[PDB]
Image (cartoon, coloured by chain):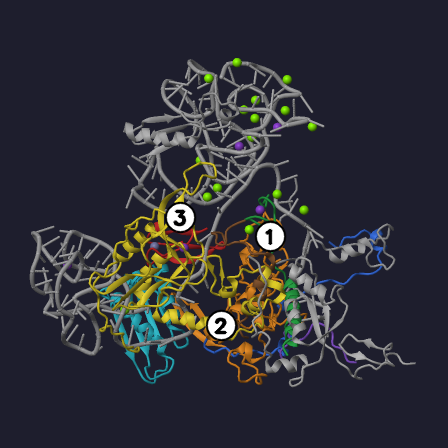
Chain colours: B green, D yellow, E orange, F cyan, G purple, H red, I blue, J brown
Amino acid sequence: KFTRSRIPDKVFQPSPEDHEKYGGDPQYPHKLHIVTRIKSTKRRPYWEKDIIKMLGLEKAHTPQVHKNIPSVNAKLKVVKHLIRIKPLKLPQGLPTEEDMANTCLKSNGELVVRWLLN
Amino acid sequence: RNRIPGRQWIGKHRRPRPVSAQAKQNMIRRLETEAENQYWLSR
Amino acid sequence: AAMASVKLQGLHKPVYHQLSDCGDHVVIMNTRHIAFSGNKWEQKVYSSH
Amino acid sequence: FKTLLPVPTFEDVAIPEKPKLRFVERVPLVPKVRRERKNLSDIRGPSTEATEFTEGRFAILALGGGYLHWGHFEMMRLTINRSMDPKNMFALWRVPAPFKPITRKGMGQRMGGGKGAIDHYVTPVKAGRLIVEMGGRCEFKEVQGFLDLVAHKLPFPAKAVSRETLEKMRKDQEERERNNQNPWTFERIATANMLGIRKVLSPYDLTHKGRYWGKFYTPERV
Amino acid sequence: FREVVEILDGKTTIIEGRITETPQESPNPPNPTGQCPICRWNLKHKYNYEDVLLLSQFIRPHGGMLPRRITGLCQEEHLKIEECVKMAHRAGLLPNHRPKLPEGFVPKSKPRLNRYLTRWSPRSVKPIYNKGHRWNKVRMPVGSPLLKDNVSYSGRPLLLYH
Amino acid sequence: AAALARLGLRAVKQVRVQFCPFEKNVESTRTFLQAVSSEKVRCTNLNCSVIADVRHDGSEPCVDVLFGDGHRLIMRGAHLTAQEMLTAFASHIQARG
Amino acid sequence: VPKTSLGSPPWPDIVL
Amino acid sequence: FKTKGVLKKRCRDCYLVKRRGRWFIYCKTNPKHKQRQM
Amino acid sequence: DEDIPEDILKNLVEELPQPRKVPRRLDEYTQEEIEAFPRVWSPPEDYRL
Amino acid sequence: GSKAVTRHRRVMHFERQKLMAVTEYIPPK
Amino acid sequence: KDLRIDTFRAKGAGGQHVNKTDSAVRLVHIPTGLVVECQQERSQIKNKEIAFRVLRARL
RNA sequence: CGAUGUUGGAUCAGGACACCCAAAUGGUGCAACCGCUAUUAAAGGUUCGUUUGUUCAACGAUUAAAGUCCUACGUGAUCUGAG
RNA sequence: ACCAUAGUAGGCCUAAAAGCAGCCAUCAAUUGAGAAAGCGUUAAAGCUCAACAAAUUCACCAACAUAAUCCCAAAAACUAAU
Ligand SMILES: [K+]
Ligand SMILES: [K+]
Ligand SMILES: [K+]
Ligand SMILES: [K+]
Ligand SMILES: [K+]
Ligand SMILES: [Mg+2]
Ligand SMILES: [Mg+2]
Ligand SMILES: [Mg+2]
Ligand SMILES: [Mg+2]
Ligand SMILES: [Mg+2]
Ligand SMILES: [Mg+2]
Ligand SMILES: [Mg+2]
Ligand SMILES: [Mg+2]
Ligand SMILES: [Mg+2]
Ligand SMILES: [Mg+2]
Ligand SMILES: [Mg+2]
Ligand SMILES: [Mg+2]
Ligand SMILES: [Mg+2]
Ligand SMILES: [Mg+2]
Ligand SMILES: [Mg+2]
Ligand SMILES: [Mg+2]
Ligand SMILES: [Mg+2]
Ligand SMILES: [Zn+2]
């Protein structure tokens, strides 16, 4: 019988060299996710299809931002082989109400508040 | 001259189609991406 | 044959098109002195019926 | 002129009475009147029973899995008895007598009706289980000579091994596993469910670590 | 180098050995701490069947190869040098290292068929009458597996079987 | 030595060995002497006299043989090896017999 | 100086 | 000859030799030891 | 072989390069090249080749 | 379909073959 | 080594089955020369089973 | 199953080699003769009769030999219909 | 490669058992050589292998036949490939 896969917690323990390799911060975890779907929900079980649907990842290659709370991370671990996850970087900080319409999200994973000024 | 008995992809006897060098690289590229996937979910 | 096939087809002209009659003559001399690599002189066979 | 190397001395080894192999009955004394399902999990996977030496110093190591019936027991018993010295060699069975019944329906009949009649009895053997264990006051070189003949005729592939050789191939299956320069291994991919590979793998592949496929054991896979 | 001279002078045979001056190794090798001659000059994994100037120093005047004891090569390199010399002879190179037989050169035969990278010998390979489809294809060997460790500037592995 | 016994030394008349044991290039001559003076080679003709001449400053290690036909094979072994000397001796036996 | 076939890269050298 | 799969020396005078791409067991004293790998 | 009719020869334009560099035999190396290549090893004086 | 344990070196699924070829052992060089 | 089995056909009435079946066994005892033929039932297995039994009984 | 006509012969044979004969060769408990066994080779050849519907088998005469098997157990829009 | 000589047909055993059906013991001359590792003999004899000396590349293991209309893309070991 084919059933769900239980991921042991030993997998999610990062090595000290992981932070330097992936550019993570050893002390402070990042705040927001950027999730992009890569593969297809077809030829995959039904429970993986629903998790993709309920995360807003219906359309492939479209970035979607999610929190870093354990509740969201619990669902991502199930479909971690179908998505690409990158941290959200803020070189200029959070956008204000004045610069909402000028925001652009670069490929490397940073949100530029002021895009193509003047 | 040499035939594959029955259908060539199902049954006890199949086609000897081997894995290629291109296929190995595709697996590794997906593995590297998923290795990074389970690091950002760690903390 | 690899370079001779290209010249005959016309795949070296930027004006190439299969419908057009573009094509170049190729003259190959000293064909008695070709050098088959490896043991292909005794292993490779040409068959016809 | 050469070097007079010391010779091994075997004076603490005691030869028990009746050193030759014990006869094994074709059928167990009390027959099994109830026909049970042909379990195939008794061959698949590594062995857990009789993987270590008890008294002797040489044994036949079973690399693969398979069934032993009364024919193979006769081949093992007769060959060893007529080829060893009863004064210096003693042998011990490491497998029980044939007990699992095997069913064979009549020749040329349509499918259906039910399980047939009991034909013979077999002994399931897993991978890594010693079959015949021999000890004595002699070196391994001469014991190896007439044990490979017995091991070659077994269904599953097998080798003639001793205490030192068995530890060396177990201490090299760990060094080859510690120094592997390949970041990805079957243990890492299968357990973590990377690439959704659990849809293709079997639930037993979590324990086998990819070294076992059916009844076949490939020792070179890390 | 020593040579043997046998002379017949009126029912008397005289056999004597004479020493001829021998060329010596070049003074300064790039890697003085090396053991065998090949890796002493940084020639490891950098020679092929074409390098006649290297393969002409480990062969006899009549096409044979010197023993490993005299040369000093390691076993791994000695087999590779042995393979290259065999491939060099079949390729048509080294024309002065054949034995001299005045009676046999006059009766010419079919013209030589140019070849290179011949793993086997011309008289020991049988035609592949039944080649086979792509799932079970009999591939004609080219070159030798002993030379798969050579440096590849292109980066693609050498295709030994084609 | 075993090669000479099989080849029939009965056709050899006299063998002499002249060498200087204190020299450096006489090792080959010593090996040739021991091979031709072996017990197996001796038991082929009980008339053949093997002479082991020993000098010090002669400086010419040499071997002289006389065959039944009447030919004089003399080889000055100073650079020759033991195998070369024995092989030449064996070759002449078959031709001259 | 050794001058083997594989000693130097086959492609022509470039000096920018 | 005797076309066989694995070659073994039946007497100490048998010598291995590779001819025509196959290994042959050639014997001088006993011609019945001649074997040929298939 | 190199026996081409004069009509064909007058039609040619350019010659394509050879796809394989032909290796040269030992007798084709100049004496300057032989002396330039280093002697890898020093054979003993008492060996017979 | 065949049983889990057979006598003829059961052919693996093609996806599993790639897994068996990407998880090989590379000795240190 | 002592039995030669000739799987020849039989004569009867079975339509397509008889014309396309070698449902007969001819047992020949090589050491003695006895010939025992059994072509009673429809299947060769039944004919082979009886033929072996008859040959042992006659010997 | 709004049809793929079914045993044996007659005619014509196509092919494989795991060869019966013809050619070359190794081994032998091969002296020669007659044999046994193994390697290599498929261009050609592989009989006529009594009984049975018979393929098969038995028997008579002979031949260098009377090979094994595939081909919708070849071949009924070519024939035969004994079964 | 080279090389083989002592007690001694060791006791027993058998028609005969001389290192070499079996039983039993397994000491001992010589710098060196097993009451014997193999072959051989009716039994002996004889050949070979361990030990002398000589001398010193390396040497565990890895061999496996064929089908029937006509084989089956053609071909290629290096000009720079995440
Ligand atoms: K199939
Ligand atoms: K086996
Ligand atoms: K029908
Ligand atoms: K024919
Ligand atoms: K005795
Ligand atoms: Mg099909
Ligand atoms: Mg497949
Ligand atoms: Mg199934
Ligand atoms: Mg009726
Ligand atoms: Mg219709
Ligand atoms: Mg017909
Ligand atoms: Mg025909
Ligand atoms: Mg044949
Ligand atoms: Mg014939
Ligand atoms: Mg028909
Ligand atoms: Mg008909
Ligand atoms: Mg009609
Ligand atoms: Mg028709
Ligand atoms: Mg009728
Ligand atoms: Mg010895
Ligand atoms: Mg055959
Ligand atoms: Mg084609
Ligand atoms: Zn022999």
Q: CA distance from mark 2 to mark 3?
A: 43 Å
Mark 1 lies within 8 Å of ligand 22 (Cβ measured):
no
Kindly indicate whether the residue at mark 3 contacts the one at mark 1 (C-beta within 8 angstroms): no
Q: Which corner quadrant of the image does residue E5 belong to? A: bottom left
Residue shown at 45%/77% (left/top)?
A: I46
Q: Residue furthest front?
A: A71
Crowdedness near tag 1: few (<14), some (14–19) or many (≥20) residues, C-alpha within 10 Å: few
Q: Position of residue D209 (x, y in %)?
A: 51, 66
Under mark 3, the amino acid is Lys
Residue visible at 31% across and 63% down in the picture? D133
Which dot marks residue D20?
Answer: none
- Can you tell which quarter of the image residue C26 is in? bottom right
Q: Residues within 10 Å of mark 2 (few under 14, many from 20)?
A: some
Local SS, label 1:
loop
Asked whether the residues under the numbered discs 1 and 2 touch, taking CB atoms below 8 Å apart as contact, a structural biologist would say no
Horizontal arrangement in the rendering, residue A13 relative to residue D19 (left or right): right
Q: Mark 3 vs ligand 23: CB under 8 Å?
A: no
Residue A112 makes an appearance in the image: yes
What numbered label is drawn on residue E137? 1
Residue indicated by mark 2: D176
Q: Quadrant of the C terminus of chain J?
A: bottom right
Asked whether the beta carbons under mark 2 and mark 3 sit within 8 Å of each other, the answer is no
Query: Numbered disc 3: what chain?
Result: H
Read off the residue under disc 3.
H2
Who's the residue at 32% across and 50% down the image? D70
**Mark 1 vs mark 3, CA separation in Å:** 30 Å
| Image location (x, y in percent) of residue F56 | 32, 84
- Name the one closer to the observer, A25 or E38: A25
Q: CA distance from mark 1 to mark 2?
A: 34 Å
Q: Are marks 1 and 3 on the same chain?
A: no
